[PDB]
Amino acid sequence: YKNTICPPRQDYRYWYFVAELTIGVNYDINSTIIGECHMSESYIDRNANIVLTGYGLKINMTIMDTDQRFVAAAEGVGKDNKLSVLLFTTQRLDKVHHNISVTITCMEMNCGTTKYNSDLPESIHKSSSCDITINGSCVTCVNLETDPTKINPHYLHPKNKYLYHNSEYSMRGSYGVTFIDELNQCLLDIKELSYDICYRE
Amino acid sequence: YKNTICPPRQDYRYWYFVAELTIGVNYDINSTIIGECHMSESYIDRNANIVLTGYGLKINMTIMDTDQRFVAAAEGVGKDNKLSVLLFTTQRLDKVHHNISVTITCMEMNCGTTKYNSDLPESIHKSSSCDITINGSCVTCVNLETDPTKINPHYLHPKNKYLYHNSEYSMRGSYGVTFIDELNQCLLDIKELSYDICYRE
Amino acid sequence: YKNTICPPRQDYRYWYFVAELTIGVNYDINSTIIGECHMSESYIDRNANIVLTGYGLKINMTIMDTDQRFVAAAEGVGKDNKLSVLLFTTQRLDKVHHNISVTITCMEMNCGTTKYNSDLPESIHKSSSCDITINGSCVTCVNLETDPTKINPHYLHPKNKYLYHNSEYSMRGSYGVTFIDELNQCLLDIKELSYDICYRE
Amino acid sequence: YKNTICPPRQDYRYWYFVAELTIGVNYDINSTIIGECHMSESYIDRNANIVLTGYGLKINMTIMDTDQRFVAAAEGVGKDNKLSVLLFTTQRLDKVHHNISVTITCMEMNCGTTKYNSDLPESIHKSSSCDITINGSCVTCVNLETDPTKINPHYLHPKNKYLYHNSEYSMRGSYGVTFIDELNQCLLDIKELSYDICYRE
Amino acid sequence: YKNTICPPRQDYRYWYFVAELTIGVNYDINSTIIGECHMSESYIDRNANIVLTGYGLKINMTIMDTDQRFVAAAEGVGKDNKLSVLLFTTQRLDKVHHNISVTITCMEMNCGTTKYNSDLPESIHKSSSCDITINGSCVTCVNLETDPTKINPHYLHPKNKYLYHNSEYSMRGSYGVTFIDELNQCLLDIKELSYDICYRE
Amino acid sequence: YKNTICPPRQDYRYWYFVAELTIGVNYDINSTIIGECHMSESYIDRNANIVLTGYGLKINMTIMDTDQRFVAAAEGVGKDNKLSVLLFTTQRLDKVHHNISVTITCMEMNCGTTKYNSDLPESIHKSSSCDITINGSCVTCVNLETDPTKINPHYLHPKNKYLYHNSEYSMRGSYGVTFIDELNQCLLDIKELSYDICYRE
Amino acid sequence: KIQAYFNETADLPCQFANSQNQSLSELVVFWQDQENLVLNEVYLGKEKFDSVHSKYMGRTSFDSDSWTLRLHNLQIKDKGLYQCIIHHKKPTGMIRIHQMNSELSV
Amino acid sequence: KIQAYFNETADLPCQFANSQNQSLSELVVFWQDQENLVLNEVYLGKEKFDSVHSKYMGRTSFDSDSWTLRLHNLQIKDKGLYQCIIHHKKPTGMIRIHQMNSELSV
Amino acid sequence: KIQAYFNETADLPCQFANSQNQSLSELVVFWQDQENLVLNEVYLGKEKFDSVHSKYMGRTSFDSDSWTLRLHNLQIKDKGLYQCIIHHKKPTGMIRIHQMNSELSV
Amino acid sequence: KIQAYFNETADLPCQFANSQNQSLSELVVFWQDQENLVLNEVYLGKEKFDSVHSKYMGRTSFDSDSWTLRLHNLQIKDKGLYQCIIHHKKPTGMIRIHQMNSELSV
Amino acid sequence: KIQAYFNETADLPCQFANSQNQSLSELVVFWQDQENLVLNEVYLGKEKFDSVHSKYMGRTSFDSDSWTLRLHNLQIKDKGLYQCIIHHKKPTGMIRIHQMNSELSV
Amino acid sequence: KIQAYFNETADLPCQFANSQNQSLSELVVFWQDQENLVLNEVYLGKEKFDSVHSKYMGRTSFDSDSWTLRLHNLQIKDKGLYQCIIHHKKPTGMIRIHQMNSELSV
């Protein structure tokens, strides 16, 4: 007997908080727009993939060799043009760190070809890596916390769904890159923040 | 002259309380959702079959060599993640015990291949058997009372329909299996319970 | 010159009270349901036919060698599980008694093959006969009064239609059969009775 | 230059009161029903034709060798089962009497084959004739006043249309037939009378 | 460089008052009906054409060798059965008088073949002509003032459109014909007059 | 790496104020109509093109060798029949002056063939040119300020969109042509002005 | 129309031409008022009085040779127009063959 | 219908022709009122009194040779029409073969 | 337009060129006011006065040789423009052939 | 059902036939009330008292040879029906194999 | 931009390069304020004063050789930026060829 | 996590393994609080104080050999967890390579 993935469905209710993606941009986004974010999921050959269109950005993030599929995402706009993305899969069936690939491509304002491409090492326990590539000059900062131990208090979960998140520090992962000569500052203010659940899937 | 089954119809009104299926799960279901359960009936070659999709579970229960067909089902969620299913056929034209097969397969949360497969003996009078098989590790307990003498008081019948149930102890049947090191506890609290009639058929 | 039948139409307004069919059943029908009865008419080769689906019963009654076609029916449920059917044709163009065939087949509750088949003699004047056959064990009593001299006072006629009934005792007909060891009792209480006009034709 | 007929149109507004058809029936019609009468017009080879379905009657009246076409009709029910039909054509372009053919065929109640067929002579000036034929025994009396000098006061004309009628006694025509041993009595009471304009054309 | 016609469009807003057509009829039109008039425009081979169906009349008026196309018309009914038509084209790009052809054909009441056909000379400056032909005996008078210097005060222009009219007497044109032994009287009372803009184009 | 254009989308939110087109006309436009202007965009072979239908004018303006595409336009009507057009592209990725071609063709009122065709030199810095051509005699004045440093205060931006404009005098461009013997006067009164955002794209 | 004179005796004639030359033996011959009350009724040559209104009851006489109804005792009220209706009684159905309207001013 | 006379003894006959010539041994023979209360009940030749209403309890006698029920002690109340119903009891099902309605005025 | 002088006699001419050279014998020649009241009416050479308004009744004279209407007794009120209308009467239909508008200030 | 007698000692037997002839060493044997409170609990031959309700705490004894629970100190309250449940503990899953319901009136 | 000095005389130059080397004979040369009131107007070499605002009426002089407008009698109010516009008058249409914005602080 | 002792001197180590064996010359080495205020900032070997919060201003010292920040003058308030973040500054982009969270209880 082996513990496997669950079959796909139209509406998933058991969500696991997998990632906190925190793109900072250099163009003006003033507030969270209701019904703005649009996500597309795929689970092909043990690779989870989510494509997020919204707030002038498209995020193509895939996780390799997982028994998880992306089922939900919530996007929110903080102060100083920061974009926080909360991602949710089905369930954590393995306690191993997974390799991550993020493609951040700029839909409007500053658009271009491959500005950046690197492998960001995992900050704590150094087990995994994040192949990041940025198509455009519209990104100041990227912060990705894989399996965080804390939800954002400004994110309200739907009443009919159930939320689970990591509780162990050993499963935490941090990836970060800055292109502006300021230490850190990728983090959100978390003062006046609102999240919107993305539309599809 | 022989007493036969009735022809199929879209809306059946004379229901017979055939079974009380009482799956306990280890994942969180907090309340009964209106319009959640979906049932599909079949009556092919003297075998009644009902497939129930709801609350993260799919229940494929078939009864062999019967003149009954499943016409209704009501699902309800009790405390401590217990799922009570009430099943209703047309009428009892025979006073013999029937062999039962239940397939409990897990749609979400803990999903997998055939965790369990056994023949549960009938507890009282030992005339029949229940071929149970459980596809996934999401089931703590299964209780099935075939032809019970008592309806749940928390189940309200529709006004336009008519309900009949067994009144003899000789026609009662009990099948039970536990996978958690706790005697019994499959039973519902029956304190704050609400039932929903499943959608189709 | 010969007096013939009228051509068919969608909505007939001149109704003639032809029959009072009074099936008693042994299963529980508690009240008259609005929009329950469904009738289908036919007039092929001088034989009138009406098929009535409702209250767990299908009634296939045909009258031989008539210049009448069934245009309306009203079903009502009395106390002690009695089912009164009022039938209406176009007009009485002949003063002769007609042979009657009733097929009472049980749709739900007690269902089966041909429980009964007989030729009921006409009680008064003995001119005609009623070939009755009952498909199922769900019938306690059958009473059929062909061309009655009195309407049920609990039946309200529609305002836009016109009603005619027999006024002569010589045109009355009574057919009756009981399968339960109780003299008569097929008659309705006529205390709290309500009629519903059947849907089609 | 010759004065000809006007071309057909969907909605005609200049009506000429051509005829007052006053069928008496022996079956019960109690009141004028709104939206009951249905008329169909034709003008083929200088013959005007109107077919009126309503109140259990179909009236197929054609006028030979005319420059008029039937554009409107209003049916009303008087006391003692009398049916008054008011007919309207376009305009009177000739001052000659026209031959009339009426077919009164019975749709419901007393129905049959050709009960009557005759040529009714015109009562005043004896210039024309009315080929009447009655298909059924449902007609007591027929009165037809072609080009009357007086409208019924109980007939209200529509506001957007215009009404013209004959003013000369020399253009009047009277045709009448009774089948019941009562002199005249075909005339309406004209006490409580209401007219309905027929639906089509 | 040459000044040409404008391309066609669905809704024209710059209207030029080209003509005042003032047909008198001998049948009763009592008032102006909202939504009665229907116009059809054409501009083929430098000939403007408008066909007006309304108030029992069809008016087929074409202007030869023009850089104008008919874009609007407003019909109104005065006292004594007079029908005033106001016509509007795009713009006046030439200061020359144009030849006019009017076909007035009678749709209802008095209908017929070509009652009249003549060339009406232009009353002032005698530069142009109006080929009039009247199909039916329903016309008492025709008055046509081409490029009038005064709008009717009873005509209200739409708020979103713009109206221009002639201001020079040298561009005025008068055509008139009477068939009734009364001098003039074609003119409207202009006491209680209301205009309706025709439907299409 | 090169900074490129952004991909097309249905609804653009980051607008750059590129041009202030200020056609004066000699026909009467009294006010700004809501929903009047209709724009069509194209970006084929590094040439931006916008076609504006509204207020009796069609404006076909293309910019050569640009990394910008026209995404928005707002038209407004000032006093003395002046038409102000505000145009918005995506973003300014180059600091070079671009060659401009405007086709102003007259839809209604004064219509014709190519009244005017010239190359207007850029007034300040003389780097570019505006190939203007005017199809019709309906234009008094044309003023085009490419990349202005000031928005009109009477133009209200939508709340969900973001607006950027030029701030440097070195990127300003002025093109102007008058056909009426009055110095300047192409400028709007800017006293009572209202703008409407055009419909498509 | 045909009128009659003052308060002595009114004569209302049908003036039936009788072009088919049929006899009075099978002919329903009767008169009526503008308010449609029956004056006389000749069914097959015998006067019938059951449908005669009480106002003209025993007041009218009939002449078969001249086909004329004589109304006696003229009043101020009976100034209306009187119409005579001639049906041809046939066993298949009774057919109206002639009608005429006369006037009466006294 | 058939009526009976005054306050001595009422005779209600079924007048069964018995065209099939079957015996009374398998025949349910009974009488009832206009308000449908059972008077007598002959099941297979033996009178049954359980369904007899208390108003006619021990008041009716039955004659098998003339097929006639004799009602004694006539009252003012029992002026209604009385109908006699004859079923033919068969083990497959009991079939009504004859019914008749008589009257009773006292 | 053509005007006339002060309170002695006004002359309103039609100034018909008569290019078709047709005679006055078949010509409807008449004058009217700005409020459209008929001054004179020459039908076939004979003056008709039935449509003449009472204000100008017996006040206007007509000269056929000069085709001119002479209006006598000028008032303060009659300062409006007067138009003369010439129809050509044809049996198929009467056709207006000429009209002219003159003024009058006194 | 099976009942027991008055206020001395109640005997509730399971009456397990043991047709598979398996030993008590792998068998979960326990009793419970109509309100479903556990009386005793035999897990693998050793009595477990953690799930025993405090009302029956230290009151019940068990006999393995007769498979019978002896309830001591009968009260007025404990007149309900008592059911004994026998599971067969297997490492893959614990399966209920027998249940029986007995009564108790004191 | 180009500025000028205090309350003696302001000099606003157009600084037209005249790269096409065309003469002033066909050139509309004029100046205007930030509130867009015309200062001077040189149409074809002759100064036109009809569009000159009354505030600058008879106050400005023009030098064709240096292409410079001299504004006399500086006030506190006229601290705005002044722009000079040079059109090239062509019979097909008048085309603006040069514009420049200068400042003025006193 | 790693903790430190009482009110003398706190030692927070990064414990960077430096598996790529790269020098401190191109490494952004800094510390921060649970409320995310910067303690020290080593950019390319030179301490930068512009982003250091005023609460820890001139209070922290840094040891490059042991890769350890010494926090002096412990207070009651600074009981939170402190995390050290090590970025690897590259001209294409600055990449975080290590982070660690230590605790501090006094």
Image (cartoon, coloured by chain):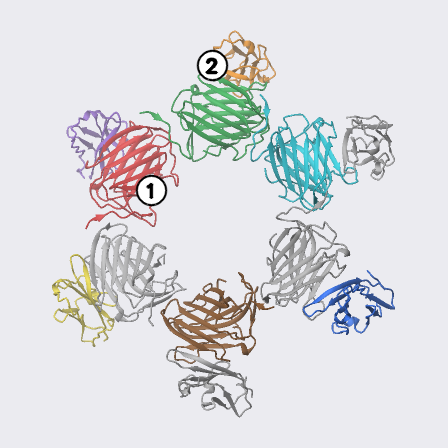
Chain colours: A brown, C cyan, D green, E red, G orange, I purple, J blue, K yellow
Image quarter where the C terminus of chain C lies is: top right
Query: Closer to us: mark 2 or mark 1?
Result: 1
Residue under label 1, please give it: E154
Q: CA distance from mark 2 to mark 1?
A: 56 Å
Q: Is residue A146 visible?
A: yes
Image quarter where the N terminus of chain C lies is: top right
Dot 2 and dot 1 residues touching (CB under 8 Å): no
**x and y percent of residue G27 in the render?**
54, 12
Number of on-image labels: 2
**x and y percent of residue D152 in the render?**
49, 27
Q: State which chain disc 2 sits on.
A: G
Q: State which chain disc 1 sits on.
A: E
Where is residue C52, by image quadrant?
A: top right
Q: Is residue G65 left or right of residue C153?
A: left
| Amino acid at circle 1 | His
Same chain for the residues at labels 2 and 1, yes or no? no
Closer to us: K40 or G97: G97
**Labelled disc at residue K41:** none
Q: Is residue J12 left or right of residue I83?
A: right
Task: Residue lying at the far top in this picture: please name it.
Answer: G65
Residue under label 2, please give it: G3
Q: Is disc 1 surrounded by few (<14), some (14 to 19) or many (20+) residues within 10 Å?
A: few
In the displayed structure, D87 sits above or below A13; it is: above
Judged from the image, the secondary structure of the residue bearing numbered disc 2 is loop
Task: Residue lying at the far front in this picture: please name it.
Answer: J21
